[PDB]
Length: 147
Image 1 (cartoon, one colour):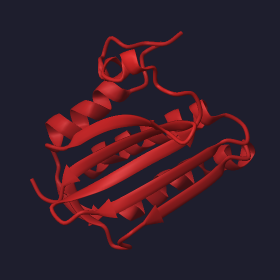
Image 2 (tube, one colour):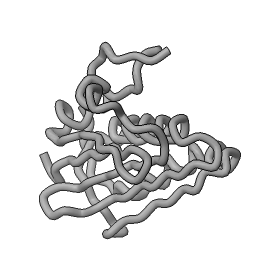
Image 3 (cartoon, helix red, strand yellow):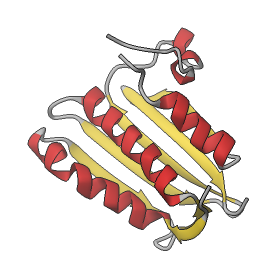
Image 4 (cartoon, helix red, strand yellow):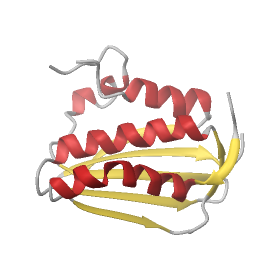
């Protein structure tokens, strides 16, 4: 694929801008925090953008009107971490892994998470997971700072 080194936080801002009207519309309380303004990562920018768009879209759909979304990005030395949290329904415990299967659907293509897992784990050698937190759900991914 096509790896470059870029400021991950500029990418997150780009994705926020794409969804700003929708977030505003829905009176969603959106927060983005980082612990390093220039959060440099070597990655396929287009592919990481796709992951972010998917996670943000899912967060907006799940949280609903007057909902809450928080994105955090963190520089951890040999890796960077992005967490996307929304208030909303929890992932059932029995579905914690299954929601990442390409065969997971809802009523109908799935939540995009199988391709997010492919991008994060297969394409970038990272990790992606979910936890139920604070009356909602976080999706977390980590990618190594360099392949």
